[PDB]
Image: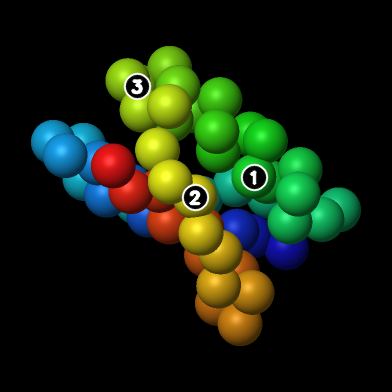
Amino acid sequence: DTYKLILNGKTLKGETTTEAXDAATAEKVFKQYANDNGVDGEWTYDDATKTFTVTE
């Protein structure tokens, strides 16, 4: 399935998507993406919309 990431850092805002097996693998990929763009963040997930949000 396609999972979505919502970036809601203090300055880093945006959305991006990735394909995954399960949600946990998508989370690991998204966390690396966020890290490479300056956000280490508080992570939440809405399974109904297959959407992760990372907040600072």
Query: Percent x, y for residue 46?
Result: 55, 72
Q: Amino acid at mark 1?
A: Glu
Quadrant of the frame with the C terminus: top left
Query: Percent x, y for residue 21?
Result: 86, 53
| Horizontal side, residue 20 vs residue 40: left or right | right
* CB atoms of marks 1 and 3 within 8 Å: no
Q: Residue at x 49, y 50 (%)?
A: 43
Measured Cα–Cα span from mark 3 to mark 2? 15 Å
Measured Cα–Cα span from mark 1 to mark 2? 9 Å
Secondary structure of the residue carrying tag 3 is loop
Image disc number at residue 37? 3
Query: Percent x, y for residue 30?
Result: 55, 38
Q: Residue at x 82, y 56 (%)?
A: 22
Secondary structure of the residue carrying tag 1 is helix
Neighbours of disc 1 within 10 Å: few (<14), some (14-19), many (20+): many
* CB atoms of marks 1 and 2 within 8 Å: yes
| Horizontal side, residue 35 vs residue 15: left or right | right
Residue named by callout 1? 27
Is label 1 or label 2 in front? Answer: 2
Q: Residue at x 73, y 63 (%)?
A: 1
Quadrant of the rendered structure where residue 12 is? top left
Measured Cα–Cα span from mark 1 to mark 3? 15 Å
Image disc number at residue 43? 2
Quadrant of the rendered structure where residue 23 is? bottom right
Q: Earlier in the sequence, mark 3 or mark 2?
A: 3
Q: Amino acid at mark 2?
A: Trp
Neighbours of disc 2 within 10 Å: few (<14), some (14-19), many (20+): some
Q: Earlier in the sequence, mark 1 or mark 2?
A: 1
Q: Amino acid at mark 3?
A: Asn
Q: Confirm whether residue 53 shows in the render.
A: yes
Residue extending furthest toward the right: 21
